[PDB]
Length: 49
Length: 49
Image (cartoon, rainbow over all chains, first blue to last red; front, side, top):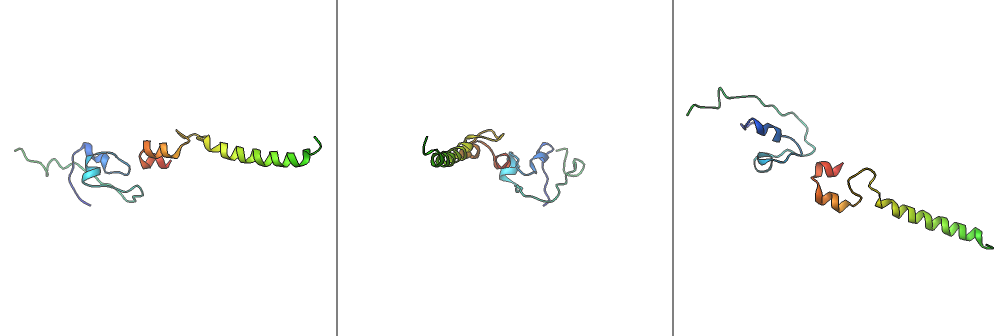
């Protein structure tokens, strides 16, 4: 599951979290197994304008 | 005290039932002994614990 979020919202991709993208964008179950991968993409997913 | 042998058995059974019912009032290290309070106060990840 691939998406782009903020830097402070990477704590919300987790079981049992309260947050905004956890509730209304992407929810993980309490019995979730797998791995969450996050890396900075300011060189690619950002524009000066 | 003529009939102490039967009364002893009656007292032991009643005391065992009273102790078993009384043990529900103990939280056993949890925040509360009431299940409804835990289910209404906490999120399921910590309410599960």
